[PDB]
Image (cartoon, rainbow, N blue to C red; front, side, top):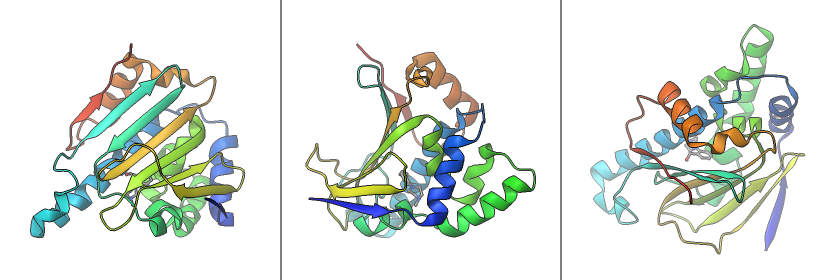
Length: 209
Ligand SMILES: CN1CCN(c2ccccc2CO)CC1
């Protein structure tokens, strides 16, 4: 059972801008998603400070980067607080409508796309490099769900029957044909060292073969 939803008009306009604007500094997508992951790990850590059973779904707090050249996917896995179904609808737990508003006035006032994270909509920078994004998530208070969108004004949500996650979020980037450099080990290491050197959780870059 798959449910199809329309993006709010402002979010559709944000993704079309991300997709269509000429902007060469695409690598910032990884910084934004890792920062999103760190924020979600912060949230479950804070909750566990007064309720340790919140970590019964997993004590380890980490970020994994999993490239797969055969599938042409880069997957960012974290064991953060995760998202409810209601969170996935309602723009993956963001205040994306007001964030897009502020972002788009900043762009007309001199800002560039790299500053997207300052407006709380950094997730959508995934579409700098991805033709399709799948988000698998598990929150302690809900079941495991799969969100998916190839942009074009709509997204789907369905119950995820795949491999259980315990708790956290998995962002699967189905990369554009000309963006496969972000599957190369040395390129990912360079981006992580450049932009994510002060993330307070272990970031593990998986290798292939
Ligand atoms: C609500 N916060 C915004 C960033 N988040 C997010 C959104 C979509 C995909 C992945 C993530 C990170 O786990 C969760 C934390």
